[PDB]
Amino acid sequence: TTGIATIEVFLPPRLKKDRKNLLETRLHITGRELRSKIAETFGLQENYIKIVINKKQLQLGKTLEEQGVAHNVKAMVLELKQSEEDARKNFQLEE
Amino acid sequence: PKVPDDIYKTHLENNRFGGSGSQVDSARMNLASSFVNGFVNAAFGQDKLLTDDGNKWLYKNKDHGMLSAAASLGMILLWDVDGGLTQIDKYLYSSEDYIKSGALLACGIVNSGVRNECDPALALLSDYVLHNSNTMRLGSIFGLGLAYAGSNREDVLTLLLPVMGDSKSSMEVAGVTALACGMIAVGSCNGDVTSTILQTIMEKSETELKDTYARWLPLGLGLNHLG
């Protein structure tokens, strides 16, 4: 429907919110915008949460259409102790 | 949390060699201590030595030992999916790429016994099941098996079929893949998996069959045809 995804997200039990939440979004945006909208809707750090879409991980540099996002698609809320790029850089420094 | 030092009750044991006979931390006793400070403190989602000092302790192991230590990392926290994944992602991004297999094992063990509707493990392993190095793929497959124990999800078996046909994978990887395919369809007699294992075992060669690692294929056959 008009290239939109009613992706349902699974917030961690640490955040006292509904385990299953419905998110409304477009499909032309990328993974970064997906996490930003997840932050705006459920109040969780965009860069500190890892989301798996349609049996696949989020692609920050790839748009929602090409990254597997679809209607009613499932998604984890993977809270990261370090941001994906920040975690990569810091743990590569810590070697 | 209980400490492995307390569990071993080293105070009570007759320390015939006091202060000199316990300063050697070999790989094997390190693996044993990891397994202890795992199983013992397991399922409580907490530990005073594994969640905070995981990486320093892990570095002291070599190859298999570090893999097992990384697996125990998540073995500490069973049944806590989101919290376990959050606490294990840091090691999943470990400096040594070999730690990644142990991190995947720990993630699968944390998810072991708990199923999430969105199934993070399959998404994590989708781009790693074909990964060239044997150990990281083994860790991903074992994470899938522990997290998805008994799922019988056709997607996992279909993805493993290329794994079964991946001659590039090593013999240990082949045994792990057979065990995972059996665990997916434990006690089901999966026709597709049945045919796959059948063809694999007939196609097997005696020269590469005499090895001790060829004993898992009947394991997978029975697991699929178990009961």
Image (cartoon, coloured by chain):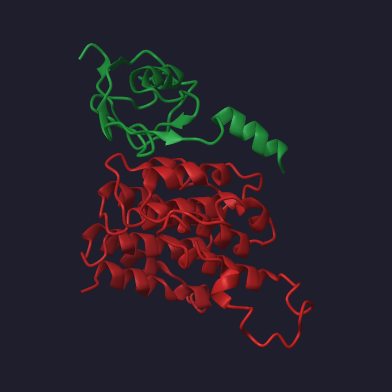
Reply above or below: B180 against B122: below
Chain B color in figure? red
Left/right of residue B97 with respect to residue B147 in the rendered view? right
The residue positioned farthest toward the right in the image shown: B20
The answer to which of B45 and B153 lies nearer the viewer is: B45
Which quadrant of the figure has residue B116?
top left
The chain drawn in green is: A
Q: Position of residue B152 (x, y in %)?
A: 25, 55
Q: Position of residue B45 (x, y in %)?
A: 43, 54
Asked if residue B125 shows in the view, the reply is no
Q: Position of residue A55 (x, y in %)?
A: 34, 38
Q: Position of residue B139 (x, y in %)?
A: 49, 55
The answer to which of B214 and B86 lies nearer the viewer is: B86
Reply above or below: B215 against A93: below
Q: Residue at x 33, y 65 (%)?
A: B197
The answer to which of A25 and B54 lies nearer the viewer is: B54
Left/right of residue B58 with respect to residue B87 in the rendered view? right
